[PDB]
Amino acid sequence: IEEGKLVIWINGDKGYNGLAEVGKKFEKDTGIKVTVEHPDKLEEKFPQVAATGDGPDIIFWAHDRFGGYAQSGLLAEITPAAAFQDKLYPFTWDAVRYNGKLIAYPIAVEALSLIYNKDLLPNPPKTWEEIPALDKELKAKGKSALMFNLQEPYFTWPLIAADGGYAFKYAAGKYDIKDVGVDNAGAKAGLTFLVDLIKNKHMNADTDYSIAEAAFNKGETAMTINGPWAWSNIDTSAVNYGVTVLPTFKGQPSKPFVGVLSAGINAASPNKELAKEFLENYLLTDEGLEAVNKDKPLGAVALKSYEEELAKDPRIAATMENAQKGEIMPNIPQMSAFWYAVRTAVINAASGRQTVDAALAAAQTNAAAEFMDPATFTYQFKNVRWAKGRRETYLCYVVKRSESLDFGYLRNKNGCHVALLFLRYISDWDLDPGRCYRVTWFTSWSPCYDCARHVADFLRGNPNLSLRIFTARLYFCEDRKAEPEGLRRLAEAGVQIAIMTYKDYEYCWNTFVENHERTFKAWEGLHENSVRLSRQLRRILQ
DNA sequence: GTTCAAGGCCAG
DNA sequence: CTGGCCTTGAAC
Ligand SMILES: Nc1ccn([C@H]2C[C@H](O)[C@@H](COP(=O)(O)O)O2)c(=O)n1
Ligand SMILES: [Ca+2]
Ligand SMILES: [Zn+2]
Picture 1 (cartoon, chains in turn green, red, orange):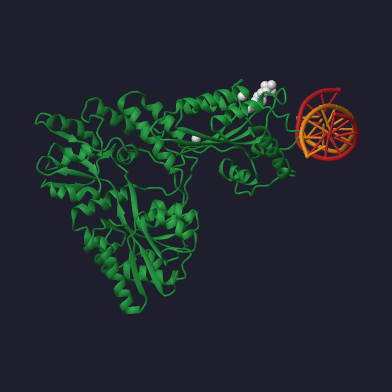
Picture 2: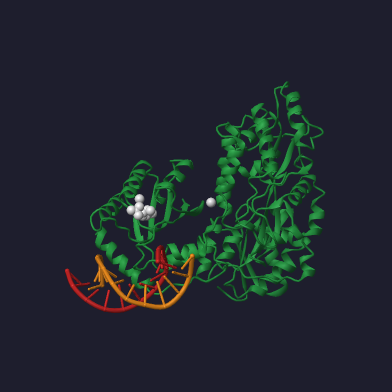
């Protein structure tokens, strides 16, 4: 990666010609040549090229991915003067904050907003409470009052979070994975209001994104909840429409998930200061953001002055208002487990195949943290000799597909070994047998014969699951004849059986245990017993 | 008095 | 080496 040269990466849907002209101005004034590129899957390409000390100097992308980029140390820390931080809206600086330090510059803002038909509705409602009544008046003209993408949780969430609902609480630049406001009085209030809308068939509950877009754009529905990304379509449908504040539930504004288009600096770049100069003095200006805007819209912008210039468009003003009344979409990994655990919980509560409090309790306990005790982990997972005197078996699990879904741990309970309890857990949890899942195990004791048979059968029945088992110790009762054949039976079923090495103990120590920012402490004889036990295992399977 | 973590010795 | 078995210091 060169010095004195700036390489900028921006997605294809965002206007790169105006940004390129900004770079031409920067080269005109300074002499540093700027080259902008719009590759494909740059959100995928950037981590790999950046891990090698290569890639772009600056990367433009939504702020949520920048958290994953920040955990991998691929983003330099920025310390812009408070005089510059005052130039942008304050809540936009929270979307570029990761682990307590700024990793990117806020550029653009996106959020859900209410899109209504001006002809059918000259005065849109300001409250969800007015929606049923209105619908009954419009169901007589052959019209629906409101239809949106009830399947995905990004669209139904604003009404849920309007009253005391949230994903994870946020002390400064910090989220708390342990606390999830999915189960709450107000969250149940919003969800039950949604269910009261779908019971009366004000919304058929089968509505997806395209059904609601075809419905609204062909004049059928009077209102739909959507973002700027679809505006262009409604502009060619010849429909006269408007964008406005999302209605308020219980008098409280609904909270959509705000996405912040951001410009981050590659940590491997030698041109960090050149990048900060370009971004602070050329991009983040009225002239820079306007030059970018004329090519392709940015929606609302974080720069106060230019956002005031753009608010003359009532649509963009609505976008910024709903953004300020909403909440920043978190950038941490657990958010994935959130989406999934909510994506089902509303659907089950939508069709009526599960009651509200059950769906929301299961959703909260699903996407939430629970961590093991450090003394408990160290006691239960010690691979030594003289470890046969341990009764309880602990199992730390990870469910992924690459989307790392729920993780946690299970222990022994009333005769039910941990493997069977995980079979009941993953069975109560529904499955979509069109996509494979990759399940990882960390066990105190390896599976016994009954557990090997039950698990191997479960694997025969659900051939989309693929399991790997890391065990601390090898268990035998009636040594040398029962368990080795059971472990070979799991081997026949295609279960990757390894014995935990040191790196596995690090992974478990930093993944499943509540360590209190304490480094992992290996005991005496860990490696010796590990190669030991791995030798016995290689002797067993092969 | 009793239970347990830990370690070493010896015989296969 | 691997597995089986006693001793011990110290904690419940
Ligand atoms: N795959 C295995 C094998 C054994 N065990 C533990 C749990 C049981 O409590 C005990 C079974 O043996 P017993 O009940 O005879 O002690 O060993 C376990 O948790 N998981
Ligand atoms: Ca969990
Ligand atoms: Zn078992």
